[PDB]
Length: 154
Length: 57
Image (tube, rainbow over all chains, first blue to last red):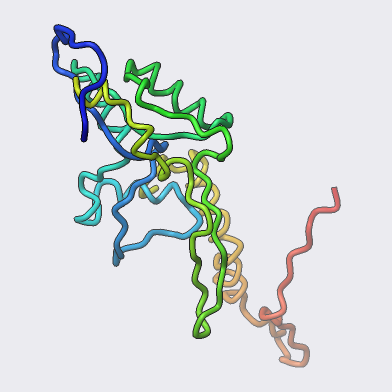
């Protein structure tokens, strides 16, 4: 927008990569309808859908923090840009990424929010239940003024 | 047994259930009606009302 940020540096190899978004534990985003359900209670049968999967679930993706962790284990260097709350679950997510040697200087804490918690209101429009968002979680509330430009430069 | 190792005692467990659930009738229905030489007195078993009582001990 205006200028740079940080001090220019020889920038160690391998080159850094930045992953932007929400840091979540598991959480498969791609959800569609499958026509071959197992028993609703006996989850010991559910592994049979892991070896005969729905086509959309043959190689599922996940949150961007998964890519950052996987990239580091493959020998790269990665930094995560995002926001977590100041609660205990937020620390656990950051400690998970620090253990995997992912840079977390781009991670901002929101001390007034609960990590991975969205406030929603339940309504009954046209005889059907729906929900609408009242307050977004800290994971989806990173502001532009909170971006770490040293990471984006490197 | 389709997606886990089955219980190691399953063969014994299913077999005993089949004996109680179906095995008793097949043998209790092969019991002949008993008639004497003179055919005066006849003894029979009403198998449809067979019962099993839980052990007292």
